[PDB]
Amino acid sequence: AAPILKDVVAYVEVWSSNGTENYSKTFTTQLVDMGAKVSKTFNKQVTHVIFKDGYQSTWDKAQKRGVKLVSVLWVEKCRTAGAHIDESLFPAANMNEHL
Ligand SMILES: [Cl-]
View 1 (cartoon, helix red, strand yellow):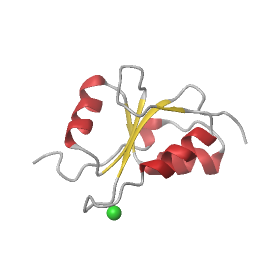
View 2: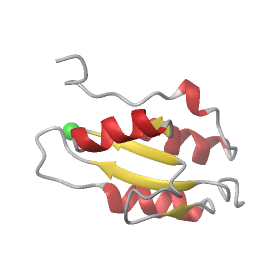
View 3: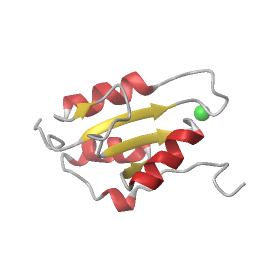
View 4: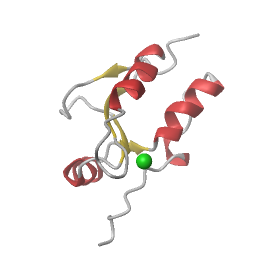
């Protein structure tokens, strides 16, 4: 138990694929438990976007702003490893990205 993600300012958009369930609150809780700040809005302070089936506008903004854009598996792996894991190993997915 340690503030391993103290330098992270996260914005979280984690949804079911069919867009009916928003699971962002539980990933928010996991991140805060590791010392991160989680922003309610995707402002200029945000360093990390945790993305699953979120808004296309969020995907695009994360890419264009050059923030770390990671899957939920990143959050789990930091937790289970007790370490700030390399974000490049956990690229987020967007099934519509090349369409
Ligand atoms: Cl799902």
